[PDB]
Amino acid sequence: MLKIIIPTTMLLPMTWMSKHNMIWINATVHSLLISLISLSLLNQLGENSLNFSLTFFSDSLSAPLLVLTTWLLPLMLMASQSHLSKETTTRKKLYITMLILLQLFLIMTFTATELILFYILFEATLVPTLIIITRWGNQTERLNAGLYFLFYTLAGSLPLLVALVYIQNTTGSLNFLIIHYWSHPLSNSWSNIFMWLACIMAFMVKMPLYGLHLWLPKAHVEAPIAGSMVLAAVLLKLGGYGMMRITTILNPLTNYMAYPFLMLSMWGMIMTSSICLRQTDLKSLIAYSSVSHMALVIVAIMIQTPWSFMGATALMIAHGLTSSMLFCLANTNYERVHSRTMILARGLQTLLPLMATWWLMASLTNLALPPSINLIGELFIITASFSWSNITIILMGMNMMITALYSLYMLITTQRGKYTHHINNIKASFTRENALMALHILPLLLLTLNPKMILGPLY
Amino acid sequence: GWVRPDLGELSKVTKVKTDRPLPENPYHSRARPEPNPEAEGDLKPAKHGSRLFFWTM
Image 1 (cartoon, rainbow over the protein chains, first blue to last red):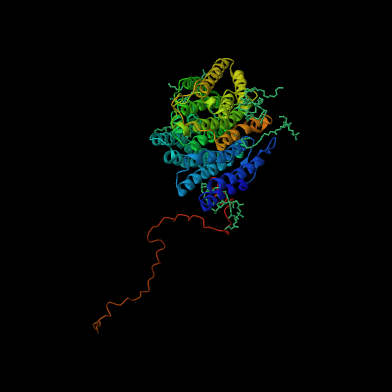
Image 2 (image 1 turned 90 degrees about the vertical axis):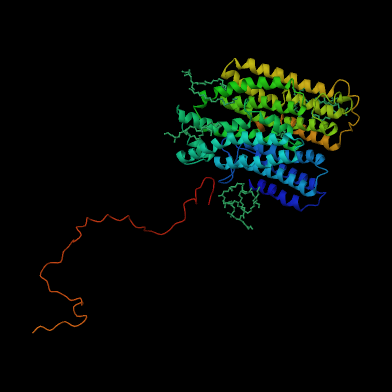
């Protein structure tokens, strides 16, 4: 993993030692180069994992996530350099440094062979994320958003730290491989019930679970565009990845401990999809849609089937790409009208035709239109849930109906109808914005040709 | 015939040729506790290092 980690670390000296006007060029070029290198991790094995050293390993679950992170960094850089054009050289370098630090922490988080190292790296992601949100966000609400995000995450994470050190003291190891191979069944007792809750709640609040999600609208809305991109695309997936890793020590306690969480997510996907139907803030609507897809991921991980895990992996990848695309599309309109209100700028298809096409593609992917990998993940999870209990088809069908309704409603209200009469500053789409959408959408569709690359290690 | 001792003679530590055996245990002492075993052997490096969590040294 050092052939990936060290180039990323080298982004910092290069960023700080480059000319004031070569900052974005250099960072973009070499982050794309690092993303090219990360693709070689997709050469996986059927049975074993890629166990490089004692401290880093890679399997079919973490390799697509690593590729997604390394890909997100350059797109972040293209999205940021517009609203940060008037900033000072040192402050731009600090923003780039925060993004690089976040990518480095995420890369080591997804490959950490030990549970406590994973914990520290997954907690380290808070610091640059919080800095981005609170320093470079636009509104006075960014401070409260930062506090919510920080303290929700930490209230989740500290009991996990206690549980992890207890597990290390009783089992002798926190090594992922050892944990799998020396797996003990978890008995039915209050001690084990609370150990389960401690092992699960941090990833629950990270995803987030419905009812523990109130930080996410604040944080994903108040953050600058790159912050929203990472928060929606890679940071939510830390909960799903960690839950997939740690559920191997929670059986058979997960059989009945998951019932409250299964109920919460199955109903809260309905609840948050309905909320999207009435959201007056475009960025808030996009933030609220992440909760439903992540609720589907929660159900898939909690029912513990090969098909459910495959669907959850594919859904995490597809949601990362699609949610980041939607945030970028909303940000392009925000940078023109300086507002997130959705009915402010209507009838945009007759002013920005290719951007309207990008909007249609993003809405279609959020719709989970087949054969997109969004649909593959959603359908696999739906089938596994149907096996788990047939009655799950009522709620999941309702959810896909409501998802269609709000996705197409957003498309219609922003792109269609009559343009607003007094808004006379909708300049033509820049090459940079169109390239941002294209680099969001093209790899999403190419994955349909090789879907096994994102179906996880249970494929 | 009694000469009077000079200054310092009466304060001397002298010796007495007694027939009484020397007391063996005048303190009536119990047996003393056995000591903790000493340290033997040569120092070898820590097996796999500190073994503190994820550290390899």
